[PDB]
Image (tube, coloured by chain):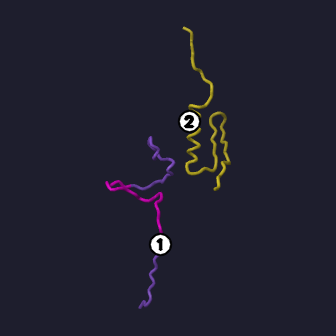
Amino acid sequence: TEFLKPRLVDIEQVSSTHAKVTLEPLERGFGHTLGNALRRILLSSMPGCAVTEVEIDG
Amino acid sequence: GVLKIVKVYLAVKRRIQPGDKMAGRHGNKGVISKINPIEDMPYDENGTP
């Protein structure tokens, strides 16, 4: 059996807005196993900082 | 006139592929747009897609 390795990645960058990763090559359902993965992880499994409570005073 | 005739019998299997018009019995036509891998198939609680 022969496996293939992910290579060539185009880091398309625009300041702080977006970066678009273009990686080749993938197979039958590999753009899925990869894409879907990042999504759920970047949503409910990614550490970060944000306000939780704000007591004005009165 | 044609004293000797030779009729050949070839054999060619033609399978099912994206683009073939398929339907049913109750009058529901259609054409397979893209036969996708069983890995994109929505499965129930069981696991059978």
Q: CA distance from mark 2 to mark 1?
A: 51 Å
> Which image quarter is the N terminus of chain B in?
bottom left
Q: Position of residue B23 (x, y in %)?
A: 37, 56
Kind of residue at badge 2: Arg
Characterize the local packing of mark 1: few (<14), some (14-19) or many (20 or more) Cα atoms within 10 angstroms: few
Q: How many marks?
A: 2
Q: Which mark is residue A10?
A: none
Residue found at the far front of this picture:
B46
Q: Is residue A32 magenta?
A: no
Q: Position of residue B49 (x, y in %)?
A: 46, 47
Residue found at the far top of this picture:
A58
Compared across the picture, whether B4 is left or right of A43 comes to left
- Provide the letter of the chain coloured yellow: A
Q: Position of residue B2 (x, y in %)?
A: 42, 89
**In the rendered image, the vertical position of residue A5 relative to residue B13, given as above or below:** above
Q: Residue at x 64, y 49 (%)?
A: A24
Q: Residue at x 57, y 37 (%)?
A: A39
Q: Quadrant of residue B6?
A: bottom left
The residue that mark 1 highlights is B11
Please give the chain letter of the residue carrying mark 2: A
Give the magenta range: B10-29
Please give the chain letter of the residue carrying mark 1: B
At mark 2, the secondary structure is helix
At mark 1, the secondary structure is loop
The residue that mark 2 highlights is A40
Compared across the picture, whether A26 is left or right of B23 comes to right
Residue found at the far left of this picture:
B26
Q: Residue at x 49, y 52 (%)?
A: B36
- Provide the letter of the chain coloured purple: B
